[PDB]
Amino acid sequence: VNGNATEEVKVLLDYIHSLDGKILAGQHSYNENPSSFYNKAKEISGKAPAVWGTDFYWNGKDNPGERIVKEAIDKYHEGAIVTLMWHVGQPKHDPPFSWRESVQGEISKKEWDDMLTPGTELFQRWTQQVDQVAVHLKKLQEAKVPILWRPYHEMNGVWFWWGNKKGKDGFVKLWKQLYDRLVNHHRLNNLIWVWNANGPRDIPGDQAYDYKDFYPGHKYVDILATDVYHGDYEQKDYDQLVKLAKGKPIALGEVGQLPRPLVLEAQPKWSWFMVWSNWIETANSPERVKEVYGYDKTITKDEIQFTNER
Image 1 (cartoon, one colour):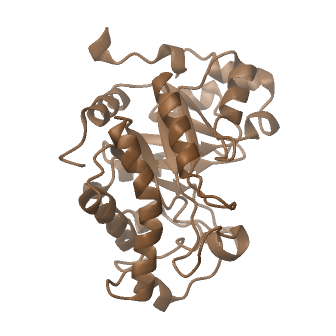
Image 2 (cartoon, rainbow, N blue to C red):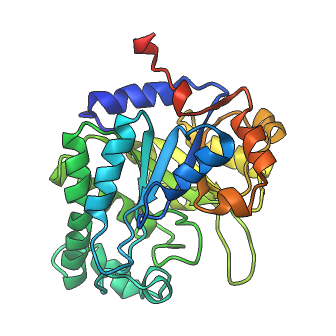
């Protein structure tokens, strides 16, 4: 969607568009030890994941960005595909951001509106929090690393402060404001924009609403993704996301229980999956990890081949 996209983004997006039934194996790690569960997945399966993921979440004393960037460049240099997300507290707060009180804290309609209104204190504070991540994305651009960038994820859920914000002044306006700041202000051209929702559900106190109610338009999204835990690979949910994506790639942005081959045969459009940290052990038997990593359509790091290198 970025006319100024770098060559590594165009190469990676062409590769993802070419998967046509194949799926990249991926693994997320907490940024405190940003490859610890990537390495565990390799120990369990015998193969390194194709996709390496971590998170800019500033939950501890120190800004994690430098540590993340150093390992992302190393993993890219090792041949992995890099994905990054960003748990973050509210503009009204400072890091480290409390999980319960900030990331999942309440936000008023006025505070939300102010964060989307240039000139207010909350908009100014929001720009500063964005810039604390942008500086690291810019270092990754200088290293020529393309990023599967998944900001403000699970936005159809009710649990995050940015969640369940409907209407033209809701989530889609936050997405576009972040897009403008990163692409136009910071001239970040190495990002692939992954709009990463949650599987919908109508559970009291724990709802996640329809995908389309939070989609900012094709102009602002490269890839659509969803998070599927408990093995809940519903065919109808897959059909809903494929319909919204209208030819854009889709992916399993987070999973716990891995998708079995039968699920992947029925749902071939998933372009990657990313297991959430130690769910690689707690939600999957070693046999299941090996079954999925060994499936003929699953691509691990050693198997990535860009068509221009053949």
